[PDB]
Amino acid sequence: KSYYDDFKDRLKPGKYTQGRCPQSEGDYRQESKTIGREHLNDDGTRSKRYTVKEADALGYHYHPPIDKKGQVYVKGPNTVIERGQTWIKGYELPSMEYTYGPKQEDIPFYPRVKLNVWGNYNLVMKVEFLFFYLPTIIVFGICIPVYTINFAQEEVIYTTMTVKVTGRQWYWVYEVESPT
Amino acid sequence: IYEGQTVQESELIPQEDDWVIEETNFCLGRNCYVRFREEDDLARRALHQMDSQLNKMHTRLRDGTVIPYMSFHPDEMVDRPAPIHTFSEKPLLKWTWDETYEEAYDD
Amino acid sequence: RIGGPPVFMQFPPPPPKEYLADGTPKTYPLHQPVFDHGYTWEHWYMTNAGVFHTVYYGEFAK
Amino acid sequence: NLEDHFDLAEYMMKMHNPMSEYLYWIAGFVSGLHGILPLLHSNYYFSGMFLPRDNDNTQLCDDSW
Amino acid sequence: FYILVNNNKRIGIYYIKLSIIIGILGIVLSYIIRVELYNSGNRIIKYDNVNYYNMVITLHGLLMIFYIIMPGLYGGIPLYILPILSVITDIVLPRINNISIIIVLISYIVVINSIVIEYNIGTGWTLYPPLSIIGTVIVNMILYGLIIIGISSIISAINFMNILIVIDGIIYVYIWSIIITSVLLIISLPILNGILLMILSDIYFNSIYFILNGDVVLYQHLFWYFGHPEVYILILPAFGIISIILSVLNNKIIFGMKSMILAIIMISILGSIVWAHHIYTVGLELDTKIYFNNLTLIISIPTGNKIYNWIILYIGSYNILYNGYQSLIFSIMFIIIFIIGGITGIIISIDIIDIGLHDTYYIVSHFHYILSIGAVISLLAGILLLKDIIGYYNVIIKINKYFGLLLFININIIFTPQFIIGFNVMPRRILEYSDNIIVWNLISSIGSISTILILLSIF
Amino acid sequence: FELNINIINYNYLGIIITVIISIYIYNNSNIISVYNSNLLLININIWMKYNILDMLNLNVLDYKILLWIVVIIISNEILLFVSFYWIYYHNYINYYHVNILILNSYNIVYNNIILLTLLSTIVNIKFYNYILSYYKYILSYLIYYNNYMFNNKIILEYKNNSNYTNDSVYMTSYFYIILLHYIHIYDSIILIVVYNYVNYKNINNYYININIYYHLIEVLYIVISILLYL
Amino acid sequence: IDPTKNQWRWCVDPAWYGGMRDKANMDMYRLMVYPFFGYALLYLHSRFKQNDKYNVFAKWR
Amino acid sequence: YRHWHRMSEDDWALPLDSMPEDVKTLMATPQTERGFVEDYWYNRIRGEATLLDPEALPSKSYIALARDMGLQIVDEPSSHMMGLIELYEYLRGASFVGPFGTIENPVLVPAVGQERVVACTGGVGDEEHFTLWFRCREGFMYRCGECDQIFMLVRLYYEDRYWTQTLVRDTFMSDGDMFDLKTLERVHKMWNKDEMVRWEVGYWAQDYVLGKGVLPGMVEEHTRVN
Ligand SMILES: CCCCCCCCCCCCCCCCCC(=O)OC[C@H](COP(=O)([O-])OCC(O)COP(=O)([O-])OC[C@@H](COC(=O)CCCCCCCCCCCCCCCCC)OC(=O)CCCCCCCCCCCCCCCCC)OC(=O)CCCCCCCCCCCCCCCCC
Ligand SMILES: CCCCCCCCCCCCCCCCCC(=O)OC[C@H](COP(=O)([O-])OCC(O)COP(=O)([O-])OC[C@@H](COC(=O)CCCCCCCCCCCCCCCCC)OC(=O)CCCCCCCCCCCCCCCCC)OC(=O)CCCCCCCCCCCCCCCCC
Ligand SMILES: CCCCCCCCCCCCCCCCCC(=O)OC[C@H](COP(=O)([O-])OCC(O)COP(=O)([O-])OC[C@@H](COC(=O)CCCCCCCCCCCCCCCCC)OC(=O)CCCCCCCCCCCCCCCCC)OC(=O)CCCCCCCCCCCCCCCCC
Ligand SMILES: CCCCCCCCCCCCCCCCCC(=O)OC[C@H](COP(=O)([O-])OCC(O)COP(=O)([O-])OC[C@@H](COC(=O)CCCCCCCCCCCCCCCCC)OC(=O)CCCCCCCCCCCCCCCCC)OC(=O)CCCCCCCCCCCCCCCCC
Ligand code: HEA
Ligand code: HEA
Ligand SMILES: CCCCCCCC/C=C/CCCCCCCC(=O)OC[C@H](COP(=O)(O)OCCN)OC(=O)CCCCCCC/C=C/CCCCCCCC
Ligand SMILES: CCCCCCCC/C=C\CCCCCCCC(=O)O[C@H](COC(=O)CCCCCCC/C=C/CCCCCCCC)COP(=O)(O)OCCN
Ligand SMILES: [O-][O-]
Ligand SMILES: [Cu+2]
Ligand SMILES: [K+]
Ligand SMILES: [Zn+2]
């Protein structure tokens, strides 16, 4: 089945580009005049006065929430008394169809399974050992060649001719011994 | 290394011959982008988002207990998208030990 | 500490809902367009939903 | 308030003004121009041409164009 | 407000946003290079304007490292999730966090303004004297940016170190990666500031450190003493992200957590004492070269352990879970790509092999595979993993197999030929080249234009 | 109950301080830089005001956080000096045989060591009084006299030296290392000018910071004295 | 002394504990934004002119 | 607790200048209607009036004596609420370690709101597993999917309020016989005579009852320069 067709009705295609009419037709920049919405603009976004120009964190509209007894309003649990016991019924979230749209049917089955863990401690320790020392053996294999080639570069040689090279911007200068 | 909880043979003995592992689906359902309603203003869309949190969901077992959404790290425990103030009450990391004191018990 | 920033506060109720003169509920900008085209495919993917759960995430062509 | 629960609530609730996105893209576009415009200006300053013709600094055949 | 915000999660977003914006200029600079290198002869840069090309490569390197990748991996993701991974509410030093992002922006504006107003010349991102100290004022401006950037990096490092005091949970592997990176900055940055001041002294205060009887090689030691820890500072946060993604998306506990943590610590200790493999061709003493070569190879041992631990995380994961998510693909791609970059690093660690491959495009390809592919993909992978938490939309990147495949194919086309060119040989930091290297340079150029087109598809 | 931390939501000094920094680059007159430096000093003071006001939160970890920050700063100062020592000793092979007059090992080193040791003793007495919840007015003015002599001696030494920064890398390193120490002495003046008695005493991060910083400056000079004068 | 009458400690950010004084100090610096832009823009013009970048076209005409 | 700072001077006693000037109404206000400062001085004035009358103490029952000093008699309900308050306060800056949770004895997770983030680390030794974080919401018996440890949320809630020391006192403490101002005067004359004031709170309190500035030296005591 096509699950999109189930909630097609909720999705009505839009009219304006980006969801707003031109400001001339409707001024969404102004604060809403509706009672209880003085902190919102006409389009529903928070007004600059509420968030910037008169932000409460800056000392505007000072109103301490806590009361004299150091209390704030707290909503209680849904309590039920049955079978000689006081029970609390937890709040279950609404069906995912309401929030997401797809109808919650024909859900693929995914069973409970505990964590996938590597076992056989003895075997695992050897693997960890190899992870460390196999690279180490490779390094040791390279070390001896490295020493040898370094010594070859710096070997003292019985040179018989010298050429002096000077680098300048932007050319090379060569000085050589002229034969007698 | 961790290899699961230790199990004793007696713990595997069933009380009935027809017991099999419960076939409860742990797929939370079918989801997609959270779809808001055009009629809902900023405040009510916030309520809508708070009611679509997967980390508030769980699976109820046959004995009434629930296995919740769980994660290795606490990054998956805040509301999505992350709110300005996340951990108002300090998350509790529960450790277990065998120590006990008499005051906790009564005879 | 008495008088300090509360560790929990209940949300105040949302502001009053707005209706047009004819009674239609007022709509607000919503950046979830319904693109127009002839494609209607629906792709579903089993997704990690923690350590012990999954969710069948669907992508719709529209 | 419920509106203040989420950081950048208007964007996250999909009500933000599109101009914010345009400015972000424009800012990126302007950043890119800082590599192209001085290239053109410097080429003209030292050569009198905004851009070279390919291989114009090398010997070209008679019919090359 | 927008600039006054101290919320760490908001600041984390700003770091990611700013890195993308600056990334465009870095991409433009990178695109200018490959267009010029399409074939022998000038293409978009006049022969009389070769100085501009030197500036392009200098800025491309500087912007990408200090202004794009480092803020993205060390400023962006860490500021968003690190206080969440810890059980704490917000960052320890909120006001310092605000000024750090503002400092990064101001330094960027100074750098780009210098392009527009000053004469355009270049000396490489390493700013080797005496060339750096005989240049024009654009070099002075770039120094101010680096010093200013250094201030932001150090204060941000101080911010993360304070998490140890307040952390109310367990120090996860990711937290360790950020902490150790902060330690590297604390020990390496002051050395960088000292030598940079000496560069300013010669440029602006008539100092004579970098003229005859003053060893110019002195700069290379102090610079690279910070230079190599920097590359490890860039990558270590990427390692932390990969560890989280692989464990989370496979529902597998991180194997050998302590081995991973010790590997990160070991890399930092070794990374602080191997800087001179950047100075093989200068003529160091025989024993000195042997020491650095030997210690440089040892860095592979801890780095190898992390690679193998990552592999076993992916092995054995449930088949039912869909494996085509972009975050998972990028995390797996990192292992494949990093191994290529690291192995080539070991090849050029052998100093005699390096004699032929120093200052060649083989070195370019080496650090591009690690940074341009690996680090970027790790940063992309982390952002994708946190898409729901961050909450961004209006992009098609979460499930886009075309983007992953095309990106992987085309970036490999750019930089695989550069390995081959290194033996041919083509020097780095060069605009013209011999006609017989065109084929490989042409192929990489086709790769560069293709990658830019792919980026437009995400929107 | 209450939240563990009283979050700080907004701040505007960061923008001002960052802009002040930019003014240094965009100046067309060195006079603007002088006045710009005063603005930086003012705004940094405001930031220090916020730290003092945070005491109202009564958070036990605030002292620890600031103390460890200072430790990191101290390390950065040490490593900065290390780089100068590194620069000095790299060219060590070129010293002592060039036709320049290096400094004497009798006059400057001894009086400076004696003078700076007295500075340490004064600060130590301040710490002891801070432990005993006690104050001595004269102590601060001894520091000012100590700093006055140090400034007077260093000014004359530079003016009467017969070799210049451009003569050799040795001279450059001598002048630069000595200047770097002076700047850290001047930073100490910036800190010590506000020393007062505060009645909340051992929960004041300023006292421990001043004691640590003054000790660092003096020990650094011992290293300088051994390297250059002796 | 009453603990519940000090809620301004957490209701108001510390940067504005001073009431109008703190706000006035913030507002004063805000007035300097555009003067700064003109000043900064002049420096760019100064460098641009001194480098003869305005004569790009006149040089080759 | 370890996460608290140093005791303030007010944590021990309040200055007399904070005493409400309308003492006559203060001693007649019901406990539920007294603020923190008013409640402090009501208990101190009434508590010290009974303690500074030695001849009556031996004949006074502990219930009456506790009431006069403002101390709350402990009972299972009040003890339960106070105990969970201190446990919540302790866990603000202390680790959360205890016995393994089972259906009979679930792990108790105190919270003020309807939700609190918790992590399960399994059992002891080998049974300990990697941290598994979950959101513990009210009204569900949570079961760890790995070790099967049982968690439960306990809410410190009562009649649209959350449990506090003052809330417990108001709910359970019952106001006794109204305080008699004659006792204040009688004890005042006992310890305050001919310029000797060994009972100073009563001296101030008696002065306020008589108006203000009536007793010797009180006008000079109340006159301030700034
Ligand atoms: C690397 C690339 C590829 C990356 C791929 C991977 C990406 C993965 C995803 C990454 C996601 C990261 C996390 C994202 C989180 C997002 C959260 C968010 O949205 O926060 C809300 C945040 C704000 O939302 P809000 O909460 O509603 O804010 C309300 C405002 O605060 C208040 O509203 P207001 O209306 O009052 O606003 C005030 C407004 C007032 O507005 C106006 O008045 C507007 C007026 C119109 C102006 C329009 C511009 C005009 C330009 C004219 C040019 C003329 C040229 C002429 C040339 C002539 C040549 C001959 O502005 C101002 O007053 C100040 C503006 C200053 C900033 C803009 C500066 C522009 C550039 C300036 C350049 C100057 C150059 C000078 C050089 C001189 C040198 C000498 O969003 C944004 O800011 C937009 C973000 C958009 C991106 C979101 C992420 C999407 C995913 C990525 C997409 C790809 C992007 C690629 C980069 C761009 C390419 C170009
Ligand atoms: C003893 C001697 C005494 C001497 C005394 C002398 C005194 C001298 C005084 C010296 C100091 C002067 C300055 C004082 C500052 C005072 C601060 C203060 O208290 O402010 C309170 C004040 C509160 O404002 P308000 O009066 O309540 O009204 C605010 C609004 O109502 C609504 O509130 P809001 O805060 O949300 O609104 C602000 C914001 C709201 O608007 C938005 O945010 C727009 C929406 C976002 C769109 C997407 C933007 C891109 C994404 C960026 C992501 C990273 C963001 C990082 C965080 C923000 C960094 C700025 O718009 C802006 O302010 C502009 C935002 C710019 C964002 C830049 C992002 C990157 C751009 C990349 C450009 C790429 C092209 C390259 C070429 C061009 C280079 C320049 O602060 C502000 O909100 C305004 C700050 C304005 C000053 C900013 C100065 C920036 C200078 C930059 C360097 C330029 C130099 C080189 C020039 C080159 C030109 C080409
Ligand atoms: C002949 C000479 C003899 C000389 C003898 C001298 C004797 C000296 C004795 C020293 C004894 C130390 C006692 C204290 C131990 C540490 C306790 C501690 O920190 O308490 C937490 C304490 C917070 O209290 P808390 O509430 O208990 O913390 C709960 C946890 O957060 C909650 O975490 P959790 O419960 O999940 O886990 C607990 C634990 C989890 O972690 C641990 O338990 C780590 C345990 C190992 C630590 C290392 C011990 C030494 C190992 C042997 C090394 C020998 C090298 C020999 C070389 C010889 C060459 C000749 O957490 C921590 O330890 C957190 C702090 C870690 C800071 C690490 C900083 C990087 C340093 C490098 C790491 C160590 C690598 C060792 C070598 C590795 C390769 C084999 O931390 C702080 O107060 C944070 C302050 C941060 C300040 C940062 C700025 C400092 C200045 C930086 C300057 C530059 C530094 C450069 C470093 C370069 C590194 C490569
Ligand atoms: C018949 C008279 C014979 C007099 C012989 C000369 C004696 C002179 C003694 C001068 C000692 C100055 C020591 C300076 C270090 C700071 C002292 C200190 O902490 O004071 C705290 C003291 C009280 O501080 P506080 O915070 O209130 O209380 C802190 C403690 O709780 C409580 O603090 P405390 O009470 O424990 O303080 C103990 C003591 C701690 O210090 C000492 O005990 C150090 C003693 C060092 C002895 C140095 C003698 C130098 C003589 C050299 C002569 C050379 C001649 C060469 C000839 C050449 C021929 C070719 O501090 C003092 O007593 C300082 C001196 C107080 C005098 C203040 C009134 C103004 C100056 C009056 C000078 C009168 C001179 C008359 C000469 C007549 C000769 C016949 O500070 C003050 O009184 C206020 C500031 C003024 C004090 C310094 C005054 C300097 C006067 C110098 C006079 C000698 C000039 C020689 C010139 C030679 C040129 C060639
Ligand atoms: C994130 C950036 C990054 C990272 C991680 C690295 C990592 C490494 N780099 Fe790189 N490097 C750069 C960025 C980076 N580098 C840059 C930008 C330059 C040029 C700067 C300039 O000149 O401008 C550079 C230059 C550079 C040079 C040449 C310097 C010169 O002369 O110009 C060398 C020489 O050895 C080198 C080596 C290494 C090594 C040995 C590693 C190691 O960390 C790699 C280790 C990883 C592996 C080896 C793979 C994983 C391990 C295994 C698969 C198993 C074990 C393997 C073995 C035992 C072989 N780098
Ligand atoms: C992070 C660092 C970084 C990154 C991403 C890149 C990316 C690229 N670089 Fe490189 N490059 C350097 C750092 C970087 N580079 C350095 C340090 C040098 C040495 C400088 C010197 O010579 O002194 C250099 C040198 C260099 C040269 C040699 C110049 C010369 O010597 O003449 C060339 C030539 O083609 C080149 C090409 C490219 C190309 C084609 C890309 C890219 O196009 C590859 C593909 C990438 C994309 C198509 C863009 C993808 C998006 C992003 C990278 C941003 C993402 C942002 C976020 C996620 C927030 N680079
Ligand atoms: C160029 C080289 C550098 C010089 C240029 C300027 C660099 C400016 C950088 C300054 C960094 C300051 C970091 C401070 C970190 C520590 C803060 C700290 O502990 O302060 C608190 C501590 C104690 O306060 P309590 O209320 O008791 O307790 C605090 C809460 N428990 O207070 C202090 O330290 C008091 C400090 C008083 C003196 C302040 C002087 C400020 C000097 C600024 C210098 C700027 C000069 C600029 C020159 C520009 C041109 C060259
Ligand atoms: C109170 C706190 C004090 C802390 C002070 C810390 C001081 C050190 C800070 C770091 C700087 C180190 C000094 C710089 C050393 C440079 C040496 C150098 O470049 O010399 C090489 C030769 O050097 C070597 O052989 C390399 C040795 C490596 C030195 C590394 C020293 C610093 C290491 C810091 C690592 C981080 C800390 C690790 C601590 C322990 C970790 C377990 C050049 O040789 P040639 O040019 O061929 O000349 C030879 C004769 N013509
Ligand atoms: O640098 O590797
Ligand atoms: Cu290196
Ligand atoms: K070319
Ligand atoms: Zn468990």
Image (spheres, helix red, strand yellow):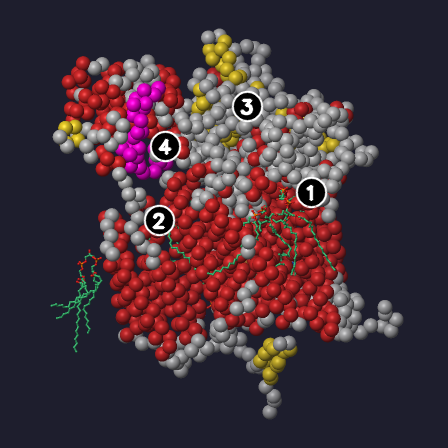
Ligand 4 lies in quarter:
bottom left
The tag on residue F205 is: 2
Amino acid type indicated by mark 2? Asn
Q: Classify mark 1: helix, strand or loop.
A: loop
Spot the residue most to the bottom. Answer: A180
Marks 2,3: beta carbons within 8 A: no
Is residue F21 positioned above or below A20 on the image? below
Tag 1 residue:
D18
Residue F138 seen in the figure: yes
* Residues flagged by tags 2 and 4 on a common chain: no
* Residues flagged by tags 2 and 1 on a common chain: no
Camera-near label (4 vs 3) is 4
Marks 2,1: beta carbons within 8 A: no
The tag on residue B67 is: 3
Camera-near label (2 vs 4) is 4
Dot 1 alpha-carbon crowd within 10 angstroms: few under 14, some 14 to 19, many 20 or more: some
* H204 sits left or right of E259 in the view: left
Camera-near label (4 vs 1) is 4
* Residues flagged by tags 1 and 3 on a common chain: no
Is the residue indicated by label 2 positioned so its CB lies within 8 Å of ligand 7? Answer: yes
Is residue A175 positioned above or below F44 on the image? below
Amino acid type indicated by mark 4? Asp
Residues drawn in magenta: H1-30
Main SS category, magenta section:
loop
C-alpha span from label 1 to label 3: 42 Å
C-alpha span from label 4 to label 1: 49 Å
